[PDB]
Amino acid sequence: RPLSELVERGWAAALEPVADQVAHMGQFLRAEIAAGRRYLPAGSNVLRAFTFPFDNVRVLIVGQDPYPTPGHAVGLSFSVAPDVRPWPRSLANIFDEYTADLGYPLPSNGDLTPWAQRGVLLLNRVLTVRPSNPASHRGKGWEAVTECAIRALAARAAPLVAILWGRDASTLKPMLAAGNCVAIESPHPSPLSASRGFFGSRPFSRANELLVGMGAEPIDWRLP
Ligand SMILES: [Cl-]
Ligand SMILES: [Cl-]
Ligand SMILES: [Cl-]
Image (cartoon, rainbow, N blue to C red):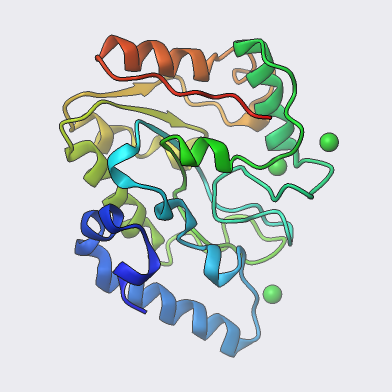
């Protein structure tokens, strides 16, 4: 299927330079199935981060690659489906920081769809993974896709705040710094860094301060 059928209209335009690379990744994914290998998330969720309006994105949260545990990854970085439990450790850690930073109670489930519908892009640098093998699809060609997404956002006039969780994420810092009105939160601890840099990092309140500072509206981070 062509790009415009896979993603939201603004995203289809922003990602038009990687239309060929997206088609090539679809061929890669068919070949993994033909070879007897599995991948996560489900085919229909791979590009799910780009099915919310491009024009509305004000915060970018970037992880490394999807959860490697079958049934966890749903196409939105760090999220899980509402009936998934226990939460993955990364997500439990994020939620601890959510409560500490903002003062809100613990969420009722692990579904970050509300963030996405409010203009947070929940991006992973690499958009698929082989089950139980983290970083197994690193260097297979998703990087050109996600680099294009990040450069297209950085090219807009509009304010953007980036939150880069981990080493793979943090490679995007110089691509982001190239744009005007782009602020990047540093340093770049992963939620699994836990008490060695992640807890107390205040990502959510910092994002909002930086957005207001740049004249944009803040994010409503509230989860039910
Ligand atoms: Cl497999
Ligand atoms: Cl839990
Ligand atoms: Cl995890």
